[PDB]
Length: 346
Ligand SMILES: C[C@H](C(=O)N[C@H](CO)c1cccc(N2CCN(C)CC2)n1)N1Cc2ccc(-c3nc(NC4CCOCC4)ncc3Cl)cc2C1=O
Image 1 (cartoon, rainbow, N blue to C red):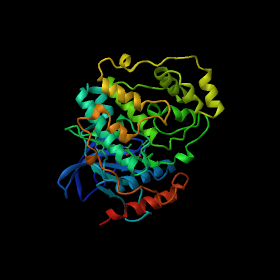
Image 2: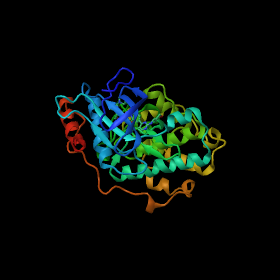
Image 3: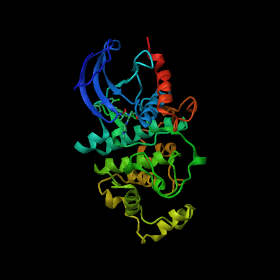
Image 4: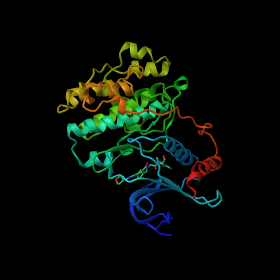
């Protein structure tokens, strides 16, 4: 068993020459030479089985990424685990190796307007496919966008992804939420469980804004501060948009705030392309019902150099989970992970 930073990384006989890349709560990631395809790959060692929420993330990632096939979505190339459920403590997921991610890039590099345009195009292209499968990614952010040395982009981490469910989207005011705070749509804090495609469009808007200036647009320090950052730029919602929020706690919170006018995008982003700011405005619309959809965004003048709907493929059918995963015990989720990964056993 090869070891990396005091941890077993047992991926042989196919994968050798391991080099450490990083780690986090999820586990650990290495590059490795793949002796079958003869190319270096990324391998992440996930050890989720003592934690129900980690099992859910692992299973969603595996089921979705194995069904999806798209140039702007990271694939799963192979999964290594023990031959029996008893002996399985870890799952190793093999994926195409990427140079960097957009979080690291925005901390270190100015993006040209052409780079911003091309990155936004690829995000929206991959998202068109995801949405066409009736799936919501639900956690789009710079660190979930991987890039190679020629700036090809792939969406990663489907651990919070789910099937769209607009009929069950309504909730009360200040309902707790899991996905990354700075990229949450305003309606999450007011009346939405984040079960519709419009949630993802908001996140992409936030990402576009961040590419424009290298700084997050709405860096909320805690749950309600996130909403207050959004309203600081968008200004007070209009009467029509406010009347859409029928829950009185949420409506009356909004009515309690002093009037704030919209901060023009060209004041926040004085060097930005005007067409980019027009698309930004449409992605960062307060009212999710008025928010631009993914296929409309691709058709926007800002992306005219790239737009080609015949080359923006959709999924062959809607994605469905067999059963709802949200509440299943971790022991049951382990079984499901075992079954989902069986096809990679020799
Ligand atoms: C978290 C998520 C993940 O695996 N998540 C899983 C399912 O959700 C998971 C399982 C259980 C828990 C959990 N948590 C814990 C709680 N936490 C709040 C959220 C995450 N997450 N990661 C980690 C990860 C590491 C590397 C790469 C990757 N990197 C490169 N190159 C490098 C080169 C240097 O520059 C940056 C790029 N090339 C290809 C790839 Cl594939 C991708 C991912 C990915 O998707």
